[PDB]
Image 1 (spheres, rainbow, N blue to C red):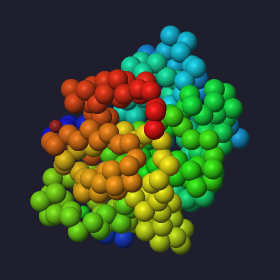
Image 2: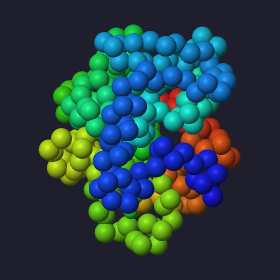
Image 3: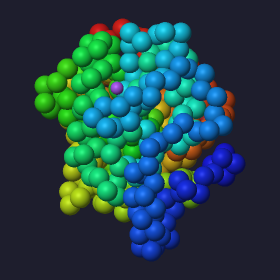
Image 4: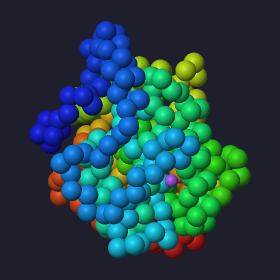
Length: 296
Ligand SMILES: [Br-]
Ligand SMILES: [Cl-]
Ligand code: NA
């Protein structure tokens, strides 16, 4: 399996019990305070800018001096993990394929920080980028829990009458943090070697800081749909989020909101982070679609 071939134990949320959860939070509190660094062995092909915004680390990737257009990238990791070395590699590839400048904020993480900290930080970097190139030249993208953050954040902009990004990209978004969709079968659960209902529940409960997991800011499947910019979603049939992605697609369609869903039946959660041909195909689909004229 691709999951096992590239496994990082320090990113696993397959917790057995409360004791594993506590140990994870203990570890993440300590690790999250450290300055995040590019992987020591990774050749990043794009040019890299190591910036900060109000003491938050922000990395920017650009290629061939192409910076007139931005992707605000919200990385996965359940709001507890920092970017994977495979996230570094994915972002590099997207930069080189799209020729947008990819912006990677290291936003506040749980267990020390909580939902409002996370969202206020994303707002600040979004505002920064809009001031640089205009909202029409900014695309928002995220994977996993980062896809949830990305959708929830654009929904916040929409609810608050803020200028919206030209497009919104969701990669294996965790649209409902409860993962209680009754269409999630045992067969589907047995195919998913990455997600854990227990792990996602427990981590998200910590981050939510007293808010119910069903709150639309946490589970954006429950958030504003009408008025969204065009949405482009990527996911696999072997991830427990798949019923939620299909449900979200149905809701977008019903509300006459533009959605492209690229659904890969045999792919795993967050598949584009893996060095496999399907990832390269997904990246090419991002590149081909990202410059489509927005006429909605
Ligand atoms: Br596939
Ligand atoms: Cl599970
Ligand atoms: Na910045």
